[PDB]
Image: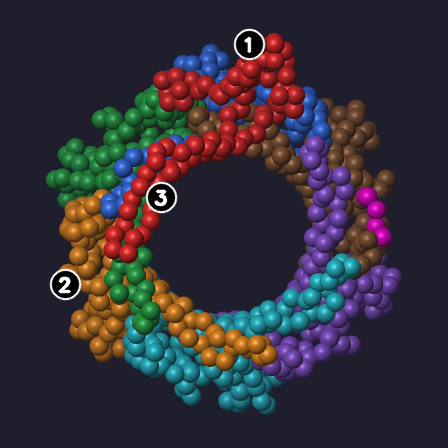
Chain colours: A purple, B cyan, C orange, D green, E blue, F brown, G red
Amino acid sequence: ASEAKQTVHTGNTVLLMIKGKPVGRAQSASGQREYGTTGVYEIGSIMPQEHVYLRYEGTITVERLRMKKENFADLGYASLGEEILKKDIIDILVVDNLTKQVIISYHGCSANNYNETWQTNEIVTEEIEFSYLTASDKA
Amino acid sequence: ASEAKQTVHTGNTVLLMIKGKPVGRAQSASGQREYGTTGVYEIGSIMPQEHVYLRYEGTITVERLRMKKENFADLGYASLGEEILKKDIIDILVVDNLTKQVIISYHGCSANNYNETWQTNEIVTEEIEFSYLTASDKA
Amino acid sequence: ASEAKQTVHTGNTVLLMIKGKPVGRAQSASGQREYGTTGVYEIGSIMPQEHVYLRYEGTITVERLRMKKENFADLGYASLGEEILKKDIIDILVVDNLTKQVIISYHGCSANNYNETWQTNEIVTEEIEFSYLTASDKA
Amino acid sequence: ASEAKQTVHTGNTVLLMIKGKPVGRAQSASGQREYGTTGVYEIGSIMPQEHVYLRYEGTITVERLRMKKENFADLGYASLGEEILKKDIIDILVVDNLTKQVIISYHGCSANNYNETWQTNEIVTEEIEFSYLTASDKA
Amino acid sequence: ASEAKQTVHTGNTVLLMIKGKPVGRAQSASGQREYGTTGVYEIGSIMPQEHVYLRYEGTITVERLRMKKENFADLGYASLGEEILKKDIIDILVVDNLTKQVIISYHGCSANNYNETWQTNEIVTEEIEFSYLTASDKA
Amino acid sequence: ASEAKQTVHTGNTVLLMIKGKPVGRAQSASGQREYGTTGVYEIGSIMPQEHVYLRYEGTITVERLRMKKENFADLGYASLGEEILKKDIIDILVVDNLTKQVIISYHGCSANNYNETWQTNEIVTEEIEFSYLTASDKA
Amino acid sequence: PQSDGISNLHRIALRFPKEGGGYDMYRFKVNPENYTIDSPQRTTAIKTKSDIVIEDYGKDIEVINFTGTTGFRPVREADGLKTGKQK
């Protein structure tokens, strides 16, 4: 029930930290990591005898409501045109609210696609998809 | 509460401008980007060494209720048949309704398609999926 | 509010004219025109430096409730078997109800697919998809 | 209002006939056609010169509640295993229930598939997706 | 209304018999049989002049709620690992409840895929997909 | 009615065990199998002569609410970056909660992917799609 | 005959000389997946300075080529129970 005793993580107990600052007014963050795991088959026997791992296909998507200013592009994480060029590697952390202990971290993200969405009446929403070199953590 | 004091863009506080003129009865203005990022895999390790960019791609989609005059053919953007070859690079902006301050610009566009629907007891619409070279912003 | 003053086109203010007659008891008409627009990329620079246009992929679909007689096939627009052969080019216009001013026109349509649908209890519905040589208009 | 005085076909006023016999407890009778139309593109211009037909394709799908007798196996249309090679060209009509006047005929068909479903507390069904050579009509 | 007089088959009047026993607590059984039927086309004439039949693509899926014991694998129809090997051909029948007259039968089924599904709170469900040599019946 | 006297597995009466330890706050445990069955077709007849197995494939997906401790990284199953190569064959069971009797085992697994979601006012989740060599059971 | 709805399929068999005189008579239990037959001709074409000359010498040696797979499941034999690998 209480924060000090619950067993499960929730949207309200986590902070998303990018380049040392908390992200404001995100809606969801989702991460897929696939090893390309594949079994090794064999003539004479129908079933595979081990799996092996191919490519570390690692991604995180961030969906966010557009802050009036200091959005990703304005504050200097997203980019447009040949700005993509200059934007060196960026680091992201997922953080446990009370203690700000690390939950997990992403050594060196990099942008894939950036989607800003305006619609009739409603709040403006933003989507970014990042691919990273290695995910990691320490306690 | 008020317009000057919120810090998220509601659909209320954004104008959409094109060929230096505001649009009446526009609906959505979705802008999507793909920097074709696909990091180099490398025999001898499981994971990508660095994530690198392979081709810029920029699409902006605008959807609008069909007005009786100054539709996107009358404003000259869209066109029917061969006449498109006579057209030139169109130009689009997203602006603060409260101060007429640019948020972002799309500095060179062309149409992909000009989808239209008439339906029983419904309002007619234009749709345009523009492709564009670059996006940028100042102030 | 009134027809004489509204700014937007609606299902009730438009007539669909085929070979000089109004279409009766249509449900929707939708038209896609895609230029195949594609950007020209370059070694050394990641972004494309212009767009160019490939093929005028132009289509209109008509969905209609089956008139008891004088439907498309009966009246002589749709066809069956080697009748497709004899049915020369057909012209379609979208017409502004009060004045019957042209909204847009399709010089020379041609059939792609024809779908007649019967179902339990309900009204019989018909679908036709047309591809045309050049869309055009005059005021 | 009345049967003789409406001018649209409701599912009430259509009979479905096959091998010169009316069907009990049929549901849908969807008839789809594709004349493979794909106009000639031509180097030196953006748009197709004329739209031309590349292959006729005709499919009629019939869906039916499984009757205890005179199912589509008992009426001989459908069949199981090799026995299909013994079958012949089946023949199908769509008729005015009020006057027993043909609307359209499908002058030569064969089965593609014979999908069936049994489910808990639900009525069983046959489905047939016939392919057909030609469709025509008189009076 | 009554079982002794109704014209239609229902979930409650059918039994599914596998290897001489009734299946308990199934939810649905569905069978697709496709002949690969294809038309033979011709230069000079756009329409096909007959159909021909390619491959007897015959399948039945069985979906069932997991009996506490004596499920498919336990009782000896489904299999795991190199057990698939030993499980010789199996026969299935669809049976008319009162008389246990045959409705249809499947000479010699064979497993394709086996899916056991556990979920929060709810009943455990099982799916098997069988492909068979020849479907057949006798009255 | 009661636990000992029902004869279908409700989600209540199943434990999910992994590395010889029960899991807290697991949700789904879907286990899918494909024996690549595709019977030999044969020129001179329409139908397959016998159905034969071409490659075993076994996937087990587990979905879980993210617990504050003893998540699938802490229990050692999942991992981030190159560290996966240090991992070994994980081992999974499905058990009778009422008697701690095995229903089935998966005698050798490896991870495909480790999908995760954080979202506004929602509970966080882990997802794992394990691949596995074989499944078996005794008693 | 092929499976035509009038007669059941029948499958290929090959007669071999038995080394003591007489024969062995082998037969396939699953028929070929691909079957190809070629009929080459010995016709030749030579081009003279003012005319073409067409010359033929008759039928050439035909070629028969086919490809298939032996069945998996055990199948009874006219004097045994032989599996696909034994066949």
Q: Which residues are magenta?
A: F86-90
Name the spot of residue B30 as percent of width and height, x first.
Answer: 50, 72
Callouts 1 and 3 on one subunit:
yes
Tell me the amino acid under the disc marked 1.
Gly
Query: Looking at the image, how many numbered discs can be counted on the residues?
Result: 3
Q: Residue at x 37, y 25 (%)?
A: D84
Q: Is residue G16 above or below residue F25?
A: above
Q: Which mark is residue C20?
A: 2
Q: Mark 1 packing: few (<14 Cα in 10 Å), some, or many (20+)? A: few
D63 with respect to E128 (left or right): left
Q: Residue at x 42, y 14 (%)?
A: E138
Comparing marks 1 and 3, which lies closer to the viewer?
3
Q: Which mark is residue G44?
A: 3
CA–CA distance in space, label 3 to label 2: 65 Å
Q: Which mark is residue G22?
A: 1
Tell me the amino acid under the disc marked 2.
Gly
Label 3 close to label 2 by CB (< 8 Å)? no
Residue under mark 3: which chain is it in? G
Q: Mark 3 packing: few (<14 Cα in 10 Å), some, or many (20+)? A: few
Name the spot of residue G43 as percent of width and height, x first.
Answer: 35, 40
Residue E134 seen in the figure: yes
